[PDB]
Image 1 (cartoon, rainbow, N blue to C red):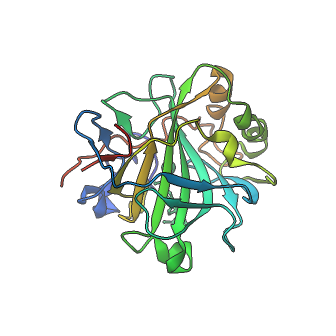
Image 2 (spheres, rainbow, N blue to C red; image 1 turned 120 degrees about the vertical axis):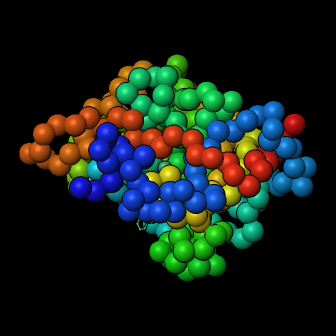
Length: 257
Ligand SMILES: NS(=O)(=O)c1ccc2c(c1)[C@H]1CCC[C@H]1[C@@H](c1ccccc1Cl)N2
Ligand SMILES: [Zn+2]
């Protein structure tokens, strides 16, 4: 009876195995745009993905992860609110059963159709497993998806999903360029938070871009054909794999006016 997104094992249950679910810096949150304060001392984000090395795509039973070689500084995030160098390890998405829901963060209570998370770890901690034990261990770049025009740089991901339909399936996924998933503007909000799934560790500097990317209805429909279940188990569509907004408790900063 492990955690998931169902009635009996979803977000309102997670605190029984993971008491930090009720902690002081949980994610996601609602971004109240009028309450966020412009921080003129915040630096532009530096997103250096030209040497990114994608390896594989995995259905882990909760989402699909596109994994990268993080054994050298090859795709890194720096600047913004960050001190030092954060290495890209993987990206994944959260999405809805309907276009009106799916994002984890919300903007003035607005839900987007989906949310992309580019996960990076602070190289001063040596490995990802050490970094998640630290309050400044991770930097997650969050990008909203709205339904409209197709995102051409997403299509190579959409077209491989048939090969990883079920939990535990993986496929080779080399030479994927994550620059094709980035909006024009790097204007962002930032706050200290957590992983949005168990183990819900409070190790994340969240950086959430203001400008969404557009994807087509056909692209997100293909996300919704994935399965939470393993092969030869009853089919349960992988939809609504998002945690709702958590209390802000004790400030969201904006990079822009
Ligand atoms: N929705 S998200 O971007 O906040 C998110 C949620 C859960 C997980 C991740 C990212 C990645 C990033 C940090 C930990 C790692 C993962 C995990 C896997 C292997 C080993 C340890 C851990 Cl903690 N769990
Ligand atoms: Zn995520």
